Image (cartoon, coloured by chain):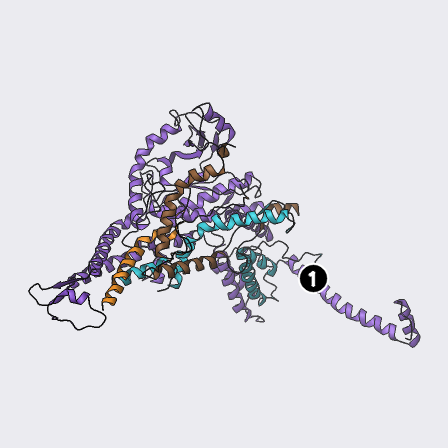
């Protein structure tokens, strides 16, 4: 155990110090956007999260998380399963062989979406995205499929990860606090013989350590509760398919964690926070009303307060004056700059004031997340569903690109429209229509495999069409022939009635 | 002016108009937790309760419940029907394999293509 | 009965202390939006709930509850029943 | 666990807590400031 000489708990404590700078930035970003989203690890139930004086941080965070959710995980088919066309065509034959295979690949895709929707991954994925925006580096773990199993999300101050400057992951440690009764019996008995008698609801720290095993590529996983491994949790995972996938946005090389998206605009949020605070402070000063009456005057304010809704009392208007806040010129200057910073922050997130500019900017934000989050999630699900026989055993030659179907529908519809225009030229003996159809498909970019009718396939169409005409014309002649024969001559009419059981005459 | 500003930002925080395409997206994140927290457990309890009282037939225990807010089933059928109707204008053409194109269209749309084709016996 | 050695009433009385911060925070929230929603457990029939000086809290809270209800539980079929396609094809 | 009649539902859930947090609590402070500003405005009208 090269990476597990000292133990899972010791690794977590040692590597926690490197996580400290990222936790502090996460709390600072949360304090301005949404304080409740990332508490500072000391906030108990009796802590109140005061709303920031500016609301663009909360409004922008919610909008960006939802816009990312729609683009990353749309309603249907954000991933595709593709087989190598050259190798698939060689092993198989042609025509519908490639089309039949795509049916199985498409059928597997529909299962993956159904599994994701049935286990409510979208709820956890949305929670992960919000943590990515504020903290920027969440961890999500996919447990083995057993009935209804939702994946777990680990916040930044719940796990720890060590990466190299090359970017590869060395080890991951997660910390969980499960009550004594909620633990399994084998673990529960181990704690009984390790820390003595335990309270029913006592929180027990459980560390799971996933580290790069020595020599061959892989990951070794084990769980320890008090100071030693449980009776059994040793699990081995390959590099591509590991349930613990640490997803980060805005990744910087040489760092073990990512940086949140808010950090790129935290300075503007701080500047807007101060300006918005002072503007509200001025209004509260304005809210107070004070009457400054000249002591050298003759008006007695005892008569004004003791009077009724209408009254004539001695006094002068010049004696009574009201203190009102000045700095009307300041208020516009502070308001103008506050509006300016709000405008640039509204564009930083996906907030309208343009329509064709926010999508293009959004395109680069989630490009990292497709490789960091979308791709590993599919890879783990593909292996896990094969093990539990949820999908047929893949031949290991299928590669999945995450597309945010695809161009196949567009190519087919575009190619059909071109053929429909070419249909206006039918009946022409000068032009080779069959060659032009092939040229059109090549220009669009279709595979042109099986779309043309072979001579054997043309015979089948004529045979099926010919059988219809024989049946259609045969039925009319047979029905009219039988009726004519039955109805000819009065005595044959009676014989025909006898055949069906009827009696001549009523 | 300050009172109006605070009202304006509080109006957006709730689902109050001043925009149409900006409040649904904010709303989408509010009830994402509630689907798993409230909708899903309620259906699971009801299904067992109705099974016990013979209100619904005994399920084979292999059925899973997604809370959607049908779904893409109708849209996929309508999308491929329109695409197939476009392929209707190309009928009578002996160069193109119409049957293969129908299969390719359904795969592009995403239908299961299970039983949608007429076998020789069904013909 | 490890969780029920002391009894149901004793557990409720003990755990009531941890509920106090949430009850107090709920009364404050209700005081500004709609005072009638969350009375403070000491309000009998002879208590009048004075209207908040601003109407944004009441208008927003009612709107958000209705919008959530409409989206969460629409007119028909906010759930569906799905069978595993691979398993169903094999059995049938 | 899957089917229990008593289902405690909470919105805005914070890990490590036995209860959820209300949605109004996030914007409670802005409501307090609006309440104070709206209060003084009406009081000025009654003086008027």
**Front-lying residue, A479 or C80:** C80
Characterize the local packing of mark 1: few (<14), some (14-19) or many (20 or more) Cα atoms within 10 angstroms.
few
Q: Position of residue A339 (x, y in %)?
A: 25, 60
Residue that protrudes farthest toward the left in the picture = A296
| In this picture, residue D32 sits left or right of residue B92 | left
Q: Check the picture and name the quadrant holding the C terminus of chain A.
A: bottom right
Q: Position of residue B118 (x, y in %)?
A: 66, 58
Chain bearing mark 1: A
Whether residue A191 is situated above or below residue A281 in the rendered picture: above
- Name chain A's colour: purple
Would residue A411 be seen by someone viewing this image from the given angle? yes
| In this picture, residue A14 sits left or right of residue A481 | left
| Secondary-structure class at tag 1 | helix
Which residue position holds label 1? A464
Residue that protrudes farthest toward the right in the picture = A491
Q: Position of residue B68 (x, y in %)?
A: 51, 54
Q: Residue at x 37, y 25 (%)?
A: A6
Q: Check the picture and name the quadrant holding the N terminus of chain A.
A: top left
**Front-lying residue, C66 or C92:** C66
Whether residue A402 is situated above or below residue C62 in the rendered picture: above
State which chain is coloured cyan: B
Whether residue A412 is situated above or below residue A381 in the rendered picture: below
- Name chain D's colour: orange
- Name chain C's colour: brown
Would residue A364 be seen by someone viewing this image from the given angle? no
| In this picture, residue B4 sits left or right of residue A117 | left
**Front-lying residue, A97 or B7:** B7
Question: Where, by quadrant of the figure, is residue A228 drawn?
Answer: top left
Q: Position of residue A449 (x, y in %)?
A: 56, 54
């Amino acid at each position: 155990e090269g990476f597990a000489e000292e133990g899972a708990k010791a690794v977590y404590d040692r590597l926690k110090n490197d996580r400290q700078p990222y936790e502090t930035r996460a709390e600072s970003c949360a304090q301005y956007t949404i304080p409740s989203l990332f508490p500072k690890d000391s906030d108990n139930a009796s802590t109140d999260y005061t709303t920031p004086w500016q609301s663009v941080g909360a409004r922008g965070l919610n909008n960006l998380a939802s816009k990312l959710m729609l683009a990353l995980f749309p309603m249907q088919s954000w991933m595709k399963l593709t087989i190598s066309e050259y190798e698939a065509k060689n092993l198989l034959g042609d025509a519908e062989g490639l089309a039949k295979v795509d049916e199985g690949l498409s059928m597997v895709e529909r299962i993956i979406m159904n599994y994701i929707e049935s286990n409510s991954y979208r709820v956890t994925l949305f929670e992960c995205l919000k943590q990515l925006c504020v903290a920027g580096n969440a961890l999500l773990y996919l447990p083995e499929p057993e009935g209804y199993t939702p994946m777990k999300l680990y916040r930044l101050n719940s796990y720890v990860v060590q990466r190299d400057a090359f970017g590869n992951v060395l080890q991951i440690v997660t910390l969980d606090k499960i009550a004594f009764n909620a633990l399994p019996e084998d673990v529960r008995s181990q704690v009984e013989a390790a820390q003595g008698e335990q309270k029913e609801d006592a929180e027990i720290d459980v560390y799971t350590h996933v580290y790069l095993n020595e020599a061959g590529d892989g990951y070794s996983k084990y769980e320890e509760v008090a100071e030693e491994v449980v009776p059994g949790s040793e699990a081995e995972y390959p590099l591509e398919e590991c349930p613990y996938i640490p997803v980060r946005m805005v990744r910087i090389d040489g760092e073990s964690y990512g940086r949140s998206y808010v950090e790129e605009y935290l300075g503007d949020l701080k500047s807007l926070e101060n300006l918005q605070e002072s503007i509200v402070k001025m209004a509260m000063i304005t809210a107070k009303v004070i009457g400054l009456v000249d002591p050298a005057g003759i008006t007695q304010v005892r008569r004004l307060t003791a009077a009724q809704s209408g009254a004539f009392v001695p006094g002068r208007k010049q004696d009574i004056e009201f203190l009102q806040l000045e700095k009307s010129g300041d208020f516009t200057v502070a308001k103008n700059v506050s509006d300016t910073i709000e405008a640039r922050l509204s564009y930083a997130f996906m907030l309208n004031s343009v329509a064709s500019e926010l999508e293009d900017t959004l395109g680069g934000v989630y490009s990292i997340l497709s490789q960091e989050l979308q791709l590993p999630l599919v890879r783990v699900l593909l292996k896990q569903l094969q093990a539990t026989q949820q999908i047929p055993e893949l031949p290991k030659e299928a590669v999945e690109p995450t597309i945010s179907r695809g161009q196949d529908l567009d190519k087919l519809e575009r190619c059909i429209a071109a053929w429909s225009a070419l249909k206006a030229l039918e009946g022409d003996d000068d032009l080779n229509l069959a060659n032009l159809k092939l040229r059109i498909a090549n220009a669009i970019g279709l595979d042109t495999a099986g779309m043309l009718l072979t001579q054997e396939q043309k015979n089948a169409l004529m045979a099926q069409q010919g059988a219809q005409i024989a049946t259609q014309q045969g039925a009319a002649a047979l029905g009219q022939g039988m009726a004519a024969q039955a109805t000819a001559s009065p005595e044959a009419m009676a014989a025909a009635a006898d055949s069906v059981g009827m009696q001549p005459g009523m």
